[PDB]
Image 1: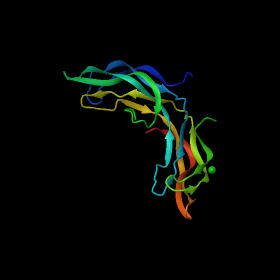
Image 2: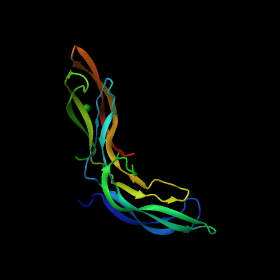
Image 3: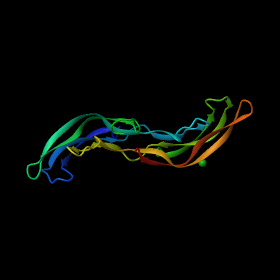
Image 4: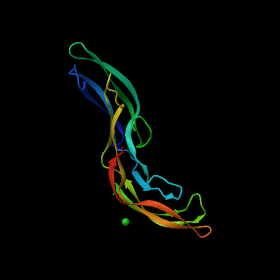
Length: 104
Length: 97
Ligand SMILES: [Cl-]
């Protein structure tokens, strides 16, 4: 299967959203693809004194499995040094939509 | 065919805490493969701008509309206990969050 959950590389320029700084081009990684598992949702039955959520669901999303934190210094007007930080995704995997993970 | 779709089925319902005679009910569920790829990419944080590590997108086959329904169970001692559930009328692909 070629369209499966996969790591893809790309480049983006990192710039501060408010301060007009010295933007920098960086190589980044993202997770992308189609998880093989179908997503589903079915009703849960409630009874007297036994209340449950209306639906029980399953859904798999292509998300980061491992990553490495990186930081880089930008140069801004006129001498300000700002650190920017982001995760460099090392591997991807399919995981439940509602998993309690940092991506959730 | 494999798209996000309504599927019908029947299930036997029993009260988990009370002795009741099971009852068969017609149910609907959502199931399928949403067309959109799911993805997750990093968010850039700065010294005073603290963000989640990732920005993600993911589509799930879930109920779009539904109807609350109810039925009377027959239980021990001529007791009638209520059970309730949502009957899914339509399905669609929706963001995980
Ligand atoms: Cl129907």
